[PDB]
Every structure is written in C-alpha cells, then in structure tokens.
Length: 260
Ligand SMILES: CNc1nc(Nc2ccc(N3CCCC3=O)cc2OC)nc2[nH]cc(C#N)c12
Image 1 (cartoon, rainbow, N blue to C red):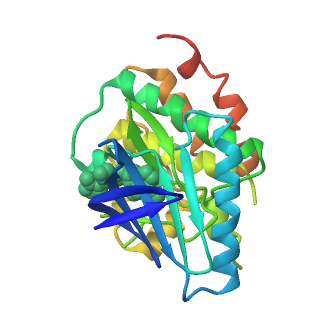
Image 2: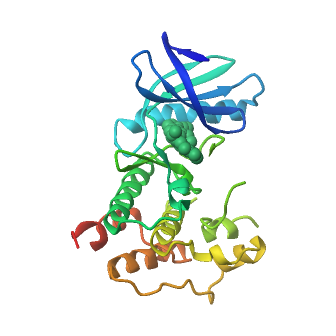
C-alpha cells in the first residue's frame, strides 16, 4: 500500500489513528524517513464538515510559523474527494504514555507543562480556544509535547472519549473563554502530578459533571514537594473562570520560571 501526495510517494507502515471519515497512518517517504499522513475521505461530507476541515488546515499552516510546539504540516493534497496531510510524526500521545501507568520525572513533567502552555498560548494568540484539550491532543516528539488538534474539526482518536477535563463553564453554559483551556490543562497537570485526574473518582458521569460545577465540592490537593506545582494546579482548577489563572499569568509563574 502507498500514498502519492503532491508528487511524492509514501508507503504505509501502520495506521496510528482513526476519526469519523479520517485515518492517520505512520508512513515512510522515498528516503525511508518517518512521517504521518492523515487521510480524509470527503465523498460523504456536509459543507460544515468541509468547512471545519478547511479552516484548520489554514490555521495549522499559519500557526506553525509561530511555534515548534504545534506539530508541523509539511504538505497537503486536497480535492473534492479526499484530503492528504503530510505531518511530522509523533512517538505516541500523552494519553497513552500516561496510561502506561508510569510515574513522571518531575522535570520532564515541568518541561511538558512548559510545552502545553507554549502551544495553547499560540493558538490563543491567533484567536482559537480548544475548549476540549485532553492528553490525546498532545504528541511526544524529541522529548517535547506538540499539539495536533485545534478542536476545530472532527478530532481523532489514537489506535469512547472522556469528560474529566470538562471546564465547569462548559457544563453550566448549556442551559467562550480562553480560561476554559486553562482548566483542561489543569486536569492534565493534576493527572500528571497525582496519577489521577481531579474528579476521576466519581465514576458515574452525571454525578461527575455536578462535582465539576459544584462550589462546596473540594478538589483534593495532597501536599507534595514542589509547592509551586501545588499552586499552579490550585489556580488552574478554580471553578470561577474570572478567578482562574490566565495563560499569560501561568507563563510568568514561579513553576515555569525559577529552575527550582
Ligand atoms: C493520533 N494521530 C497522530 N499520531 C502520531 N503518532 C502516534 C500516535 C499514537 C500512537 N499510538 C497509539 C496507541 C498505540 C500507539 O503506538 C502511535 C503514534 O506513532 C506511531 N503522529 C501524528 N502526527 C500527526 C497526527 C495527526 N492527526 C498524528
């Protein structure tokens, strides 16, 4: 099996992930180098799908001029029938590496943190709010964390979703803020520090949504050595969006700034 994209030929090692219409494969180029290719079959596709897929290709194009922490889009073929995106290839997604129930070198966790902030800050700077960041949204390449889905299109799953990372304003605002990504980054850090996400314990997802949106519900923050990390997690995970810490604040925080 093979894939010709904008004149170049790539051979399919392994499918890595799937989506609605999409498939992402790990492939080699004519020079036995690693890439990822995302395939989207557009034959069946509303114009909103079409429009969403179009948008983020463009945003991905611009956005990678501004940050190493966004995965690169080398090339793309697009026609009325399919999309091919030749992209830099991750090693695995944060959500799989996390579930290799490991424990994290405290200075890799700090560097991964730095990485998510850089990347989310970048999309924020060009007007994007993911409002659904999860570990699946991050790839590990060269001991960096790089972002892949800007939450715009029909997002993929690496080869059932999740709601521990839902910002309370997301639950409340059903009957957007950049601060709602701080929350989900919050849960991913919390997860990364305490081996579990905040309300990961309320296993019935009605009672879990309430907890998230519930004032006299208390997230537990077990004391730990890096008390700066404890403060970050504590200000990320405030229920009041206006009381929650901004991304530009987080970037001026002792946790990322002082080399402990
Ligand atoms: C998920 N989509 C992507 N995935 C990867 N890498 C990768 C991700 C996951 C895994 N898994 C998953 C469980 C077992 C295992 O190995 C393996 C992987 O590499 C072989 N690189 C990418 N670049 C652009 C992408 C898009 N869109 C993209």
